[PDB]
Length: 177
Image (tube, rainbow, N blue to C red; front, side, top):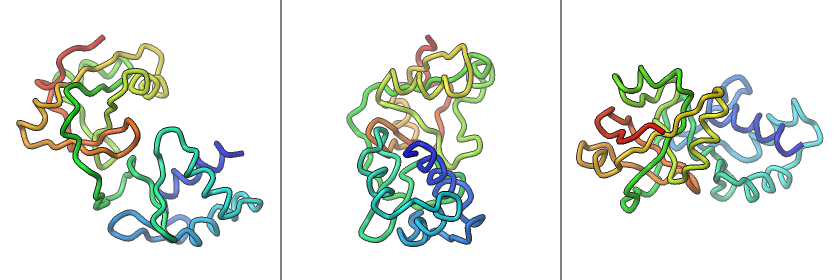
């Protein structure tokens, strides 16, 4: 039940709020009341406290509540003005992806694709688990974070391990494992 409701929250908060009549503010927030009411049209037993539980217990840091408003911290496919802190300390960052994507990435770098930002991770396991969602022969990309910063692509702390960055040029990918 938690996972099914969380997946619908991510759909609403990252991709298609307008399908439920919701319009996030410029920071990506909708009111908690609005979200609960939207979830109840699919899952009527859902309550504000069950959503609050999902947010508190989420292992990746998917969601953020500020008072009576809630957003997804990352993953959006519509423009959002996020106020996340910059990651200045990480030396290496990681991105897992199916091997089938590697030829394009070596030419183009990582691109945000359908999302606003490229997503990477401080954590090798999480990076690989993310890649495995997409396919079977996952490669672990090692990314030189200082290479990104030097080129004006600041990295932001979007989640426990999740990091977002405008893009990753291929010169900043040091290894594919």
